[PDB]
Length: 53
Length: 438
Image (cartoon, rainbow over all chains, first blue to last red; front, side, top):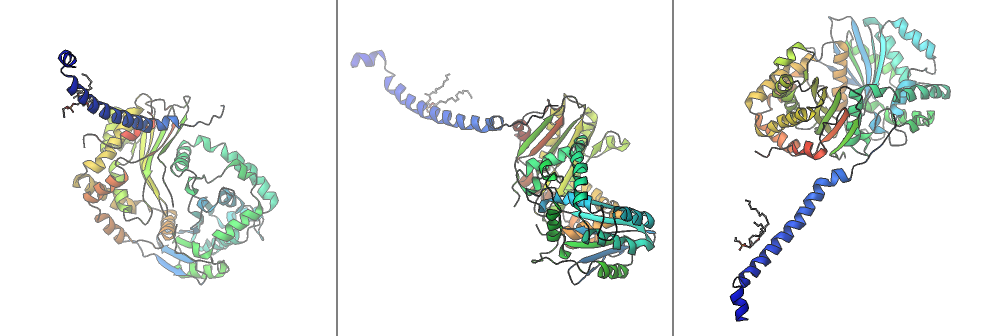
């Protein structure tokens, strides 16, 4: 355990910052999906009627 | 100061409204009805328009030929039009031919034959009208605009109706429509020009006394529309001119923002490259458009109905690579109604409107149309003094407040027709309805 700490002394801080990053990034991923779908819905919902000239 | 509009009622509830002008020698008399295509359902859509055709196809007494002769002998003409909420049938004649014309109108409205033979004959005429409105680009654009803005609602239907209904309209449904809707409490007999009010009331008692009253008489101009932000694109690369309309939900006739919406509409105003004065107009949009050649024309509108309206602009342009600029600058001028307008623009537009609202009424038909429209939408003729007061009460604060709730960041209905490849998708147009800098 001690030598593992010596090799990677940032370990404890790194993992706690990782937890914060995971949470924020996940939330932003969810919101970016909502916002993409919101903006794209006029394209996805488009309908056509063709009357051959 | 114009002569007073006199108004009387009959017992059935028919209103008679008149404005005499002893300086003219002609008179416009007619019947303004508070009914139109909106009163149809989806099955009889087109009935109101169909009836307008058959009204001139012969009555219980006079045949079609006799009808023609009678009007020709009077010397003037008859005219009729059906809209979404209003039907009009009028007669322009000489001063002393007014009793004849009232008699003819009463006859075609109350005692029309609606013979199966005539129904069948008109069914082809009206079918042909479906394939010839296609040319009237402005009408095409505005019919699609209503269809999309009021999606699957009565205001969204066309007046002509679908092809299917035209082939299946019977004399029964025609008779039912006009019996339910053309009731005395929904009708106004209007005279303008060389008419005596007292003479007109006598003629009304003689000809329109046996009109049915409706079971539940509501006041004149009594109506829920749910506007849909949406677009219709009718791209046609072979047309040289693009026609584009953009609208938001506007105001009804009796809205408290009625005049504020008219003032806002006048700040943007109209433009036409063919008119010599248009390059010098005060409107900011007009200056941008003329300096950059962005359009052949634009026309601001504020159309009202009993319970809703559409407020927007209609553009025509040959500049097919700068349609984006045209629409961009138009919506940026609308943004300024929320962010920037001050007493400068507002007082200017009020000045222009104070005159405009009076100027419009420059002949007997225009006056009759004004009386009839006001009586069927408001239940009264609003005097120029009242109109001058309502306009004076519009402040810059009112315009900004109105624009911030009606235009700013709101859904639009958008119709484009013609070479509209340069018109961006819905989102990019609708994003111009606000300013990120504000």
